[PDB]
Picture 1 (spheres, rainbow over the protein chains, first blue to last red):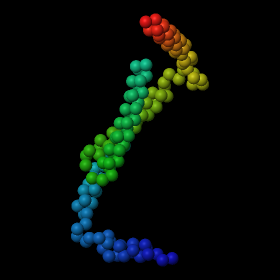
Picture 2: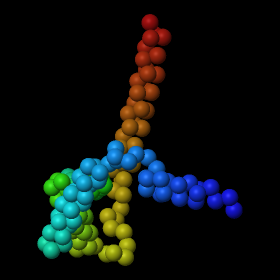
Picture 3: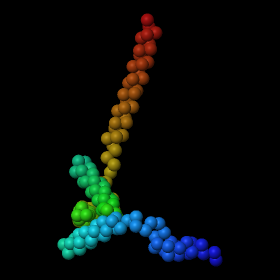
Picture 4: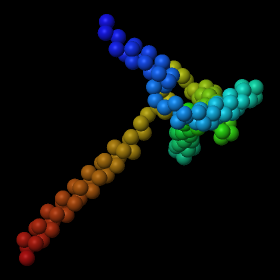
Length: 50
Length: 105
């Protein structure tokens, strides 16, 4: 009934939505991952159509 | 003999290449990309195994109810054991004769 993990998760989500870093995040890595995911989705759609 | 071992090595290499292609596809589509397209070919490699399955499906299947290759043909093996035993007996007799000759001196 202590629920310390719930409080830690709430604090991590409420401080900066990540609890570590505000402007030094992985936004560029996230964009690269999104581009890679779009390319993989296009390749998978082509493979399915083939 | 030759063809059976060749087909076995071919199936083993096919399985190894399928596992390697799956690992490469996982490593590529996991994190970072046009090379991921070749990852789809990995799935095609899986289809190759299916063909091998078909190759195993429409294989010989001589009886499919019993075991083929009747007889171990080890009669030749038994004959070879007898030949080696005769060679050992001859070696023993020769050693006895040699001991007798050395004692004669």
